[PDB]
Length: 106
Length: 106
Image 1 (spheres, one colour):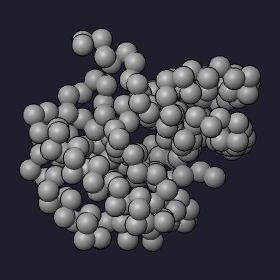
Image 2 (cartoon, chains in turn yellow, orange; image 1 turned 30 degrees about the vertical axis):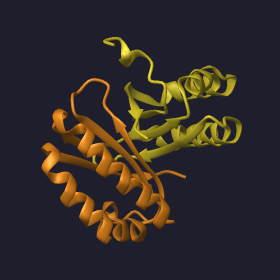
Image 3 (cartoon, chains in turn green, yellow; image 1 turned 90 degrees about the vertical axis):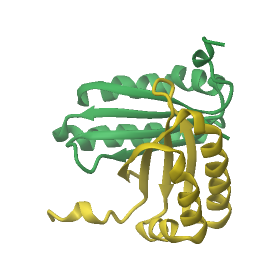
Image 4 (cartoon, chains in turn purple, cyan; image 1 turned 180 degrees about the vertical axis):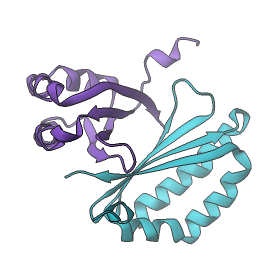
């Protein structure tokens, strides 16, 4: 049906493009890696959570993420450590994030 | 040094944006999923190999890929099954692929 895009029932991919101030990259990476270790350790529904750096745009990062389900993604976005990390990261940002959700094909 | 971008010594992420003819999506997905099963089964250096569909652009797919090293990526691109799959997939394409390589942060 035409509202199918709202809730894919399979795995959910994400490319999160983050624009970080280059001078604050070290700070950003430390907070992010600490978050990622928590995500991987605590969330069985998070299948991939991988920070990467752009090769061409200064201070740009792309996070590759994969979740088992919408339920796993909903949980992910609401944890106290996710919220704390976001608060710690915000001041390092140069611009608004661009998040793209994708339907994983299996 | 200034030529560092040429060879990241850690893990290599990829977002491969593929533009498929919508009418040939079923054909494309069958060939791609068959390829992905081979990749995952045969290549210990391939850590992630996940086909996803765009939620907004018709016939657009993004493959999320992660390799242990440049060596693992070099191997990946040269296998007989990768080459055979590419030949099978080509005729389904609507436009040129856009591949972005990323330095994984760990």
